[PDB]
Length: 49
Image (cartoon, rainbow, N blue to C red):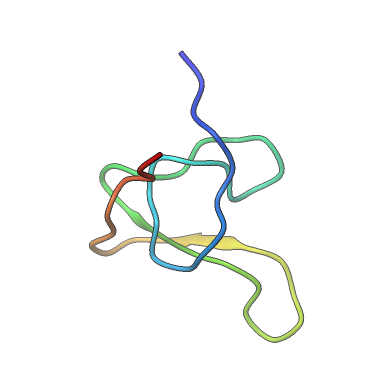
């Protein structure tokens, strides 16, 4: 199964690093400082539809 892409910071079940899935068990942050997304451990909500 594959999820969709992210659109905000804090999501979880989506695609942060290129096309890799980073969600449950961790937290994802989008473009930090004009940079790309990053998978940081924490508490994030899945990606609704």
